[PDB]
Image (cartoon, helix red, strand yellow):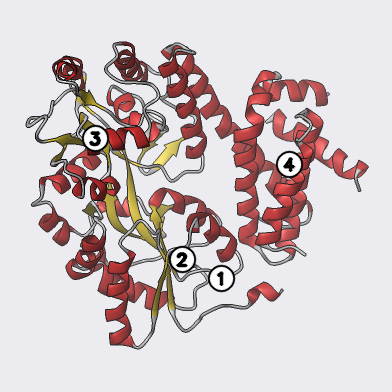
Amino acid sequence: LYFQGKIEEGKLVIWINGDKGYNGLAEVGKKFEKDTGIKVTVEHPDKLEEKFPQVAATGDGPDIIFWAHDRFGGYAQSGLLAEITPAAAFQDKLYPFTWDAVRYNGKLIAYPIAVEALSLIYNKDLLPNPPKTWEEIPALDKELKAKGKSALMFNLQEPYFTWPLIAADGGYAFKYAAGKYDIKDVGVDNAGAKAGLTFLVDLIKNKHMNADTDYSIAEAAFNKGETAMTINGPWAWSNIDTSAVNYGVTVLPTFKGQPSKPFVGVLSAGINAASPNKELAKEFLENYLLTDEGLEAVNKDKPLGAVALKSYEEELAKDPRIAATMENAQKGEIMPNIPQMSAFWYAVRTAVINAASGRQTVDEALKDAQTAARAAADNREIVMKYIHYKLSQRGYEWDEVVHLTLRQAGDDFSRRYRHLTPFTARGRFATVVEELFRDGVNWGRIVAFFEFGGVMCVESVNREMSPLVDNIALWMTEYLNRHLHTWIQDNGGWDAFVELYGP
């Protein structure tokens, strides 16, 4: 049980991505160090959002982690984030919708900092008045094509950027009802989604946009003055500042009279559930960072976009680019922090690419994506039921015909085939699963996949490493939805598994 030892208990350790204003954050940390005597260390490790589950599962890692709120759902699932109950006088200082972004299972698990949303960015010299509607963009592109320019270029390869148009007329990921997501209700292939994606493919068919345009092509074309408009977030502003392009930022165009609905990421600060410095961390976030002066120091280094603190958001909003960022956020929806979201994104990414290349119609592309998103939700329930059953066999409490049939097949596999740390569990999981499906996928090796994951979850409880159980559940859910689902659908689905193994 050597993992119980700790590192750097005398300093407040902070993890924040390198593209954020960490030097401005460090400046806030220096003021905190002077007033308290406790040294603040701001680190920006590469891939810190993937390292945090490993280090935090043994009571280690940073005292505070900064990241978009949607990734904090998985952290709160494993119990890696401390539950905060800030005073009402402090909660009233931030916008209510930002607190909703940091609430998991009815508990606040982070402090919201900044509000990031996509906006319409336009070249003021090519287009002094940007269009209010998507519908007028084809006619606008005609005029600019005569002058050797184009109307709009943005990243078509990632559904984060195309979803605002797809959602405008009625598309949705998971129905959101009073702080909860109905994972059985997916709006990927409804009438509104089809209308938005059809408008997008029509732009490509009418040569107003190209299907190969990605982030790098769109950013380079805009920043050199070749296209009049782009769709992007505050993270892209710095590169346009140093270019010769004089750009504005405004509300996204409407589709069929309805607002574009981008998904909103809320930069948030979570406190490590096992940090010995939780009170110091809460003191730093509430009394130093989340003030006008603290947010200004970070925003001056790298623009935060809109902020959760009302007093400083009203000051920032005097610049139309910030008022536009907030306005598109208000017209959009907070990014769901549920784990069924990553499979939604994989499904819609394939659908948009296939529809834009002409390999599928809009109807078939979205129908595939609708089924994939829903089936990936059922796959997670299969994982969670399997692990709960495997832990209940050894008397461990932890948070229809397919479940029963897979249980018995797994018990049969352990009959015929009768140290652990978060770092070693990840390595062995990647090693065994790779060896299982290197020469193909079949039902027998899927059953071996569930049994291997179940047994490893049991050993995690034995080593007093409960958060690793939820880490493993996520790894299994990811691999099943990314590398095994296509084979399952093409081989008859889980019903074919029951018909081969069930009575």
Q: Residues within 10 Å of mark 1 (few under 14, many from 20)?
A: many
User: Circle 2 — which element?
Assistant: loop
**Residue labelled with disc 2:** 82
Q: CA distance from mark 3 to mark 2?
A: 42 Å
Q: CA distance from mark 3 to mark 4?
A: 42 Å
Which image quarter holds the C terminus?
Answer: top right
**Residue labelled with disc 3:** 222
Q: Which mark identifies residue 244?
A: none
Q: Position of residue 171 (x, y in %)?
A: 35, 25
Q: CA distance from mark 3 to mark 1?
A: 43 Å
User: Circle 3 — which element?
Assistant: helix
Q: Which mark identifies residue 434?
A: 4
Q: Looking at the image, which residue is at 37% across and 42% down?
A: 335
Q: CA distance from mark 4 to mark 2?
A: 34 Å
Q: Amino acid at mark 2?
A: Ala
User: Circle 4 — which element?
Assistant: helix
Q: Looking at the image, which residue is at 31% across and 23% down?
A: 170
Looking at the rendered image, the disc whose residue lies closer to the viewer, 1 or 2, is 1
Q: Position of residue 79 (x, y in %)?
A: 53, 60
**Residue labelled with disc 1:** 60
- N-terminal of the two: label 3 or label 4? 3
Q: Amino acid at mark 4?
A: Glu
| For residue 322, side relative to residue 497 (left or right) | left
Asked if labels 2 and 3 touch by Cβ distance under 8 angstroms, the answer is no
- N-terminal of the two: label 4 or label 1? 1
Q: CA distance from mark 1 to mark 2?
A: 13 Å
Q: Amino acid at mark 1?
A: Asp
